[PDB]
Length: 304
Length: 5
Image (tube, rainbow over all chains, first blue to last red; front, side, top):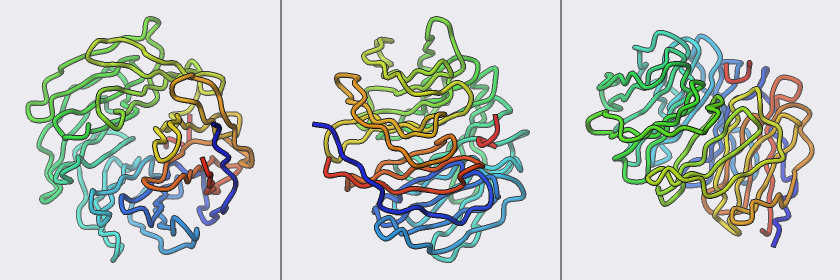
Protein backbone atom coordinates (compact mmCIF):
# COMPACT_ATOMS: atom_id res chain seq x y z
CA UNK A 1 0.00 0.00 0.00
CA UNK A 2 0.99 3.55 -0.85
CA UNK A 3 -1.53 6.35 -0.42
CA UNK A 4 -2.49 8.30 -3.54
CA UNK A 5 -3.09 11.83 -2.27
CA UNK A 6 -4.21 14.18 -5.01
CA UNK A 7 -4.92 17.92 -4.92
CA UNK A 8 -8.45 18.83 -3.83
CA UNK A 9 -8.09 22.59 -3.40
CA UNK A 10 -5.68 25.49 -3.05
CA UNK A 11 -6.79 27.97 -0.40
CA UNK A 12 -5.56 31.52 -1.02
CA UNK A 13 -6.16 34.57 1.12
CA UNK A 14 -3.32 35.15 3.56
CA UNK A 15 -1.12 38.11 2.65
CA UNK A 16 2.06 36.68 4.20
CA UNK A 17 3.57 33.25 4.81
CA UNK A 18 1.18 30.81 6.47
CA UNK A 19 2.52 29.39 9.73
CA UNK A 20 0.13 26.62 10.78
CA UNK A 21 -2.88 24.61 9.63
CA UNK A 22 -5.10 22.55 11.95
CA UNK A 23 -8.25 20.48 11.49
CA UNK A 24 -11.03 21.02 14.01
CA UNK A 25 -11.89 17.90 16.06
CA UNK A 26 -15.33 17.48 14.45
CA UNK A 27 -13.54 17.53 11.10
CA UNK A 28 -15.48 20.19 9.20
CA UNK A 29 -13.09 23.09 9.64
CA UNK A 30 -9.49 23.98 8.85
CA UNK A 31 -8.00 26.87 10.79
CA UNK A 32 -4.90 28.69 9.58
CA UNK A 33 -2.60 31.26 11.21
CA UNK A 34 -0.17 33.50 9.38
CA UNK A 35 2.65 36.01 9.69
CA UNK A 36 -0.05 38.41 8.48
CA UNK A 37 -1.48 38.42 12.02
CA UNK A 38 -4.70 36.75 10.90
CA UNK A 39 -6.53 33.50 11.53
CA UNK A 40 -8.76 32.12 8.80
CA UNK A 41 -11.36 29.36 9.04
CA UNK A 42 -12.05 27.19 5.99
CA UNK A 43 -14.37 24.34 5.10
CA UNK A 44 -12.41 21.11 5.44
CA UNK A 45 -14.36 19.43 2.63
CA UNK A 46 -15.23 22.23 0.21
CA UNK A 47 -12.20 24.42 0.92
CA UNK A 48 -14.63 27.31 1.24
CA UNK A 49 -13.43 30.44 3.04
CA UNK A 50 -15.60 30.98 6.11
CA UNK A 51 -14.17 33.88 8.10
CA UNK A 52 -11.19 35.90 9.28
CA UNK A 53 -10.42 36.29 12.98
CA UNK A 54 -8.09 39.16 13.87
CA UNK A 55 -6.73 40.94 16.92
CA UNK A 56 -3.07 40.01 17.39
CA UNK A 57 -0.55 42.83 16.97
CA UNK A 58 2.12 40.75 15.22
CA UNK A 59 2.57 37.52 13.27
CA UNK A 60 1.08 34.28 14.60
CA UNK A 61 3.15 31.08 14.81
CA UNK A 62 0.51 28.57 15.86
CA UNK A 63 -3.15 27.81 16.55
CA UNK A 64 -4.95 24.89 18.22
CA UNK A 65 -8.57 23.75 18.64
CA UNK A 66 -10.43 22.97 21.85
CA UNK A 67 -11.85 19.45 22.18
CA UNK A 68 -15.33 20.68 21.22
CA UNK A 69 -14.28 22.54 18.05
CA UNK A 70 -15.76 25.66 19.64
CA UNK A 71 -12.61 27.42 20.82
CA UNK A 72 -9.30 28.35 19.23
CA UNK A 73 -6.05 29.44 20.85
CA UNK A 74 -3.25 31.30 19.08
CA UNK A 75 0.41 32.01 19.84
CA UNK A 76 1.84 35.30 18.57
CA UNK A 77 5.05 37.34 18.39
CA UNK A 78 3.19 40.09 20.29
CA UNK A 79 4.04 37.97 23.33
CA UNK A 80 0.48 36.86 23.97
CA UNK A 81 -1.80 33.94 23.23
CA UNK A 82 -5.47 34.52 22.48
CA UNK A 83 -8.51 32.35 23.13
CA UNK A 84 -11.17 32.82 20.44
CA UNK A 85 -14.84 31.89 20.20
CA UNK A 86 -14.85 30.28 16.75
CA UNK A 87 -18.48 31.09 15.84
CA UNK A 88 -18.47 34.79 16.77
CA UNK A 89 -14.80 35.25 15.99
CA UNK A 90 -14.26 37.51 18.98
CA UNK A 91 -11.39 37.26 21.47
CA UNK A 92 -12.60 35.80 24.75
CA UNK A 93 -9.25 36.28 26.50
CA UNK A 94 -5.68 37.46 26.07
CA UNK A 95 -3.06 35.41 27.92
CA UNK A 96 -0.20 37.62 29.09
CA UNK A 97 3.00 36.61 30.83
CA UNK A 98 5.57 35.49 28.27
CA UNK A 99 8.47 37.91 27.87
CA UNK A 100 9.11 37.10 24.20
CA UNK A 101 7.47 35.49 21.17
CA UNK A 102 4.97 32.74 21.93
CA UNK A 103 5.76 30.02 19.42
CA UNK A 104 3.45 27.10 20.15
CA UNK A 105 0.22 26.20 21.92
CA UNK A 106 -2.30 23.43 22.63
CA UNK A 107 -5.38 22.66 24.74
CA UNK A 108 -5.33 19.55 26.93
CA UNK A 109 -7.99 16.90 26.17
CA UNK A 110 -10.20 18.37 28.89
CA UNK A 111 -9.77 21.75 27.19
CA UNK A 112 -9.72 23.57 30.53
CA UNK A 113 -5.99 24.22 30.20
CA UNK A 114 -3.67 25.70 27.60
CA UNK A 115 0.05 25.00 27.30
CA UNK A 116 2.42 27.41 25.57
CA UNK A 117 6.04 27.52 24.54
CA UNK A 118 7.96 30.71 23.95
CA UNK A 119 11.31 32.11 22.90
CA UNK A 120 11.66 33.18 26.54
CA UNK A 121 12.63 29.53 27.10
CA UNK A 122 9.68 28.81 29.38
CA UNK A 123 6.57 26.66 29.09
CA UNK A 124 3.44 28.07 30.73
CA UNK A 125 0.20 26.35 31.68
CA UNK A 126 -2.92 28.56 31.57
CA UNK A 127 -6.47 28.28 32.88
CA UNK A 128 -8.87 28.58 29.95
CA UNK A 129 -11.80 29.88 31.99
CA UNK A 130 -10.00 32.78 33.67
CA UNK A 131 -7.12 33.34 31.27
CA UNK A 132 -4.71 33.27 34.22
CA UNK A 133 -1.30 31.60 34.16
CA UNK A 134 -1.25 28.70 36.62
CA UNK A 135 2.38 27.63 36.09
CA UNK A 136 5.58 28.85 34.46
CA UNK A 137 8.06 26.03 33.88
CA UNK A 138 11.80 26.86 33.48
CA UNK A 139 11.67 24.25 30.72
CA UNK A 140 14.69 24.89 28.49
CA UNK A 141 17.83 26.93 27.85
CA UNK A 142 16.74 28.13 24.40
CA UNK A 143 13.49 28.89 22.53
CA UNK A 144 10.71 26.30 22.91
CA UNK A 145 9.63 24.99 19.51
CA UNK A 146 6.66 22.83 20.53
CA UNK A 147 4.35 21.88 23.41
CA UNK A 148 1.85 19.02 23.54
CA UNK A 149 -0.46 17.27 26.01
CA UNK A 150 -0.72 13.47 25.93
CA UNK A 151 -4.11 11.76 25.55
CA UNK A 152 -5.15 11.84 29.22
CA UNK A 153 -3.79 15.32 29.94
CA UNK A 154 -1.47 14.12 32.70
CA UNK A 155 1.63 14.76 30.59
CA UNK A 156 3.17 17.55 28.54
CA UNK A 157 6.03 17.19 26.09
CA UNK A 158 8.23 20.09 25.03
CA UNK A 159 11.01 20.45 22.47
CA UNK A 160 13.68 23.11 22.23
CA UNK A 161 16.57 24.52 20.25
CA UNK A 162 18.66 23.46 23.27
CA UNK A 163 18.52 19.97 21.76
CA UNK A 164 16.29 18.50 24.44
CA UNK A 165 12.82 16.99 24.57
CA UNK A 166 11.23 16.96 28.02
CA UNK A 167 8.28 15.19 29.57
CA UNK A 168 6.51 17.12 32.33
CA UNK A 169 3.96 16.12 34.93
CA UNK A 170 0.99 18.43 34.25
CA UNK A 171 -0.32 18.56 37.81
CA UNK A 172 2.98 19.42 39.50
CA UNK A 173 5.01 20.85 36.66
CA UNK A 174 7.98 18.67 37.65
CA UNK A 175 10.19 17.14 34.94
CA UNK A 176 9.71 13.38 34.55
CA UNK A 177 12.20 12.84 31.74
CA UNK A 178 14.79 14.57 29.58
CA UNK A 179 15.81 12.95 26.28
CA UNK A 180 19.09 13.47 24.49
CA UNK A 181 19.72 12.75 20.81
CA UNK A 182 23.49 12.18 20.93
CA UNK A 183 24.73 15.24 18.99
CA UNK A 184 21.87 17.23 20.58
CA UNK A 185 20.86 19.17 17.43
CA UNK A 186 18.02 21.77 17.78
CA UNK A 187 14.64 20.08 18.20
CA UNK A 188 12.18 21.85 15.93
CA UNK A 189 9.07 19.88 16.81
CA UNK A 190 7.77 17.15 19.11
CA UNK A 191 4.43 15.45 19.73
CA UNK A 192 2.93 12.36 21.43
CA UNK A 193 1.73 9.44 19.32
CA UNK A 194 -2.04 8.90 19.35
CA UNK A 195 -1.75 6.21 22.05
CA UNK A 196 0.62 8.38 24.07
CA UNK A 197 3.43 5.85 24.39
CA UNK A 198 5.69 7.49 21.78
CA UNK A 199 7.06 10.89 20.92
CA UNK A 200 7.77 12.03 17.35
CA UNK A 201 10.59 14.60 17.30
CA UNK A 202 12.05 16.63 14.45
CA UNK A 203 15.64 17.85 14.62
CA UNK A 204 17.25 20.43 12.34
CA UNK A 205 19.61 17.80 10.94
CA UNK A 206 17.04 16.74 8.31
CA UNK A 207 15.75 14.03 10.55
CA UNK A 208 12.57 12.83 12.30
CA UNK A 209 12.52 10.27 15.11
CA UNK A 210 9.94 8.15 16.90
CA UNK A 211 10.96 7.62 20.53
CA UNK A 212 9.65 5.38 23.29
CA UNK A 213 10.28 8.16 25.82
CA UNK A 214 9.84 5.85 28.83
CA UNK A 215 12.71 3.62 27.69
CA UNK A 216 14.61 6.39 25.96
CA UNK A 217 14.77 4.25 22.84
CA UNK A 218 14.56 5.31 19.20
CA UNK A 219 12.25 2.89 17.37
CA UNK A 220 12.14 4.51 13.93
CA UNK A 221 13.75 7.24 11.87
CA UNK A 222 12.37 9.12 8.88
CA UNK A 223 14.74 10.90 6.54
CA UNK A 224 15.02 12.05 2.95
CA UNK A 225 13.22 15.37 3.33
CA UNK A 226 14.90 18.73 3.96
CA UNK A 227 14.71 20.28 7.39
CA UNK A 228 17.55 22.32 8.83
CA UNK A 229 16.08 25.81 9.11
CA UNK A 230 12.38 25.99 10.06
CA UNK A 231 10.19 24.41 12.73
CA UNK A 232 8.06 22.17 10.52
CA UNK A 233 5.03 20.35 11.90
CA UNK A 234 4.95 16.54 11.65
CA UNK A 235 1.96 14.22 11.94
CA UNK A 236 0.66 10.71 12.49
CA UNK A 237 -1.78 9.75 9.74
CA UNK A 238 -3.95 6.94 11.08
CA UNK A 239 -7.21 7.22 9.14
CA UNK A 240 -6.10 4.73 6.49
CA UNK A 241 -2.67 3.17 6.31
CA UNK A 242 -0.31 4.26 9.08
CA UNK A 243 1.88 7.07 7.80
CA UNK A 244 4.16 9.80 9.05
CA UNK A 245 3.50 13.14 7.35
CA UNK A 246 5.66 16.26 7.26
CA UNK A 247 6.37 19.38 5.27
CA UNK A 248 9.84 19.97 3.80
CA UNK A 249 12.15 22.85 2.86
CA UNK A 250 12.31 21.64 -0.74
CA UNK A 251 8.64 22.60 -1.25
CA UNK A 252 7.15 19.10 -0.97
CA UNK A 253 5.03 17.16 1.49
CA UNK A 254 6.61 13.89 2.59
CA UNK A 255 4.68 10.76 3.50
CA UNK A 256 6.51 7.82 5.08
CA UNK A 257 5.43 4.28 5.88
CA UNK A 258 5.49 4.37 9.69
CA UNK A 259 6.79 0.80 10.10
CA UNK A 260 9.24 0.49 7.20
CA UNK A 261 10.41 4.13 7.33
CA UNK A 262 10.06 4.05 3.55
CA UNK A 263 8.98 7.18 1.67
CA UNK A 264 5.70 6.23 0.01
CA UNK A 265 4.78 9.56 -1.58
CA UNK A 266 5.93 13.16 -2.12
CA UNK A 267 3.26 15.77 -2.85
CA UNK A 268 4.31 18.45 -5.38
CA UNK A 269 2.68 21.82 -5.99
CA UNK A 270 3.75 24.33 -3.34
CA UNK A 271 6.34 26.92 -4.43
CA UNK A 272 8.07 27.43 -1.08
CA UNK A 273 8.93 25.67 2.18
CA UNK A 274 5.99 23.58 3.36
CA UNK A 275 6.00 24.75 6.98
CA UNK A 276 2.87 22.98 8.14
CA UNK A 277 0.71 19.94 7.49
CA UNK A 278 -2.25 18.46 9.33
CA UNK A 279 -4.09 15.15 9.04
CA UNK A 280 -7.88 15.03 8.95
CA UNK A 281 -9.31 13.22 12.02
CA UNK A 282 -11.58 10.86 10.05
CA UNK A 283 -10.87 11.14 6.32
CA UNK A 284 -7.67 10.51 4.38
CA UNK A 285 -7.19 14.23 3.79
CA UNK A 286 -4.05 16.33 4.20
CA UNK A 287 -3.72 20.08 4.67
CA UNK A 288 -0.38 21.69 3.82
CA UNK A 289 0.74 25.34 3.92
CA UNK A 290 3.85 27.16 2.67
CA UNK A 291 5.90 30.28 3.26
CA UNK A 292 6.19 33.73 1.67
CA UNK A 293 6.64 32.83 -2.01
CA UNK A 294 3.53 30.65 -1.78
CA UNK A 295 1.17 31.81 1.00
CA UNK A 296 -1.36 29.21 -0.09
CA UNK A 297 -2.88 26.22 1.67
CA UNK A 298 -3.52 22.95 -0.17
CA UNK A 299 -5.98 20.17 0.62
CA UNK A 300 -5.05 16.71 -0.60
CA UNK A 301 -7.21 13.60 -0.64
CA UNK A 302 -6.30 9.92 -0.89
CA UNK A 303 -8.00 6.54 -1.11
CA UNK A 304 -5.07 5.53 1.04
CA UNK B 1 7.45 34.22 13.39
CA UNK B 2 7.74 30.47 12.76
CA UNK B 3 7.75 31.72 9.17
CA UNK B 4 11.14 33.34 9.69
CA UNK B 5 14.35 31.48 10.43
